[PDB]
Image (cartoon, rainbow over all chains, first blue to last red; front, side, top):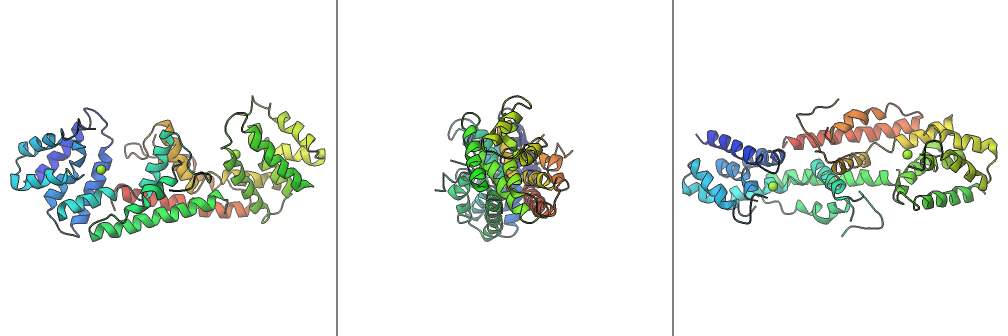
Length: 188
Length: 188
Ligand SMILES: [Mg+2]
Ligand SMILES: [Mg+2]
């Protein structure tokens, strides 16, 4: 059955992430996948495709060299046997990474906003060696600026409704956060 | 007048931070100072002392070597002329870094909780090279754990009321945050 495939595929990614990078990028893959589910079950679209897609968009991305991963995913959907009628659609949106696709994309972009985002940011900021905030460098290179820079404007690129909904809630939190963050910056 | 001293002293720290470390640790010094004010003006204690203290607790800390900064602050309060009757109290609490002191300490510890804290954390996490969260490593080395580790238990060490109040509000936010952070971790 399909679930047995969507299952073994969960092993396919979980593994390939070990022969290199890190089996830590999985928690991201899943978060998007579980999210693509909840999104479909409120917007429609072919689940299996949505799932199989969200689960392999990353394997084609540090995979190798350009569209070299496509055939990497291509020849895989084969081993798992998937009528070209569907596969052609699965490994399709995996390129632009269609209601099915539209949802996967809403499930991936959503995974940038919210608490996690805030953290992902200052975190990436720490590694990259930068401050968190600086009144000498207003928004348009500190970590707090990145929010206005290319994050708060992500809730406007959501496609389906469920995604847009969640996005507004997530987006709102980053707003209120930077609101609580600032008052503290000035000891309020 | 005193304000002219609390002012020139603002220059004393602002400068010494340039001959080494970074004039970036100032935004922390101030945040505590402005905070020690708002706190006194609601709890009492000798302002000037509170201010002069909060403003120099850090200069005695990467200053040099052990209690070598004490005389660094000591001989300074002299140049600014400050009756030993007060100086003895100012550079005093600067050691344990008394209602005046009690407030400075409440104004310094508070500067660890809240949005900034959250950020300071993942930030320090990024630099130190660690994940943000990991279900394989429960609380008691990811950045999220540090919260329960030695942060959420800081609102219990506050002395005066105003500090305790603010602390509860600040503490609450870190709670709700880790609450919004988690739901996202499981795509809620
Ligand atoms: Mg992704
Ligand atoms: Mg301090």
